Length: 308
Ligand SMILES: [Zn+2]
Image (cartoon, rainbow, N blue to C red; front, side, top):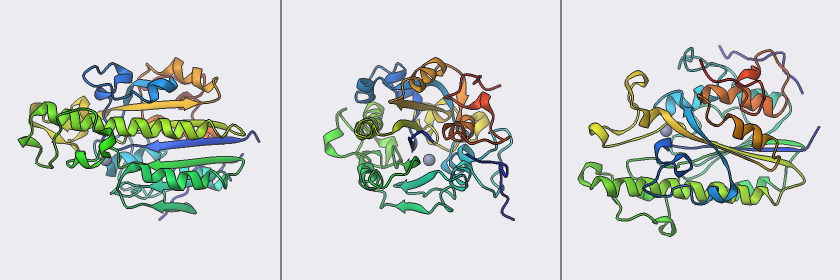
């Protein structure tokens, strides 16, 4: 059975939301949030982006996180067996222009399947996403959501995620055989991947400022965190309930040229939020009218409260 959701949904202003779904990035290594060893957020710091310092993920592996964050279900009631429409289907059926560009080696895990304009790239440098993004910026409609799904910090071959121009933190760990590396070198490599992702964000913002015929927003969040040898744990996917915050505590970053959203975002940044919030935030952004919309979960809505 393929269940439909928000069957009562419907929708003016010229709007553009760029949703960036990250990969393996963990909040603890964001300088936007007070990480001091390496300045990982050098680029988006210059755009005064809003950083959510208390943002959690739905799961500890892509297979749970990616579908769940886009699903109507929150972490406590999500099941992997559910097979139904997600936030993107609701925006599409409600007439919003939806594009999904995927550079992630794992795919969209079924989220993008029913979109008309979706693309899979080769999972090389994330910068390749800027190509179909620029091309979609020519054929915009009145309301658009563009999803960019990053390879981001995918491990264990971290050193392959960024070009030499962003090997800024050294020495590095240029192997998948992570336990052989000094831990500082491993961290440096991991931080470089964050830096590269940070740069790409500000390049997205940079293209967004050339589009002022529209109200433009960037929302970036990771699917989950990552362990880097602390307590002998590597990679991710540890069962959520026993997982270290390294795997569940993720970055979330918002930017808009509409600085009223920018200041609603700034007001919420310290609240206990999570991927649970993505569903209503995405409906709310394109003003989708429906009963499944929960105003107290929309990040860009004054009635937003923290998670229970
Ligand atoms: Zn993942």
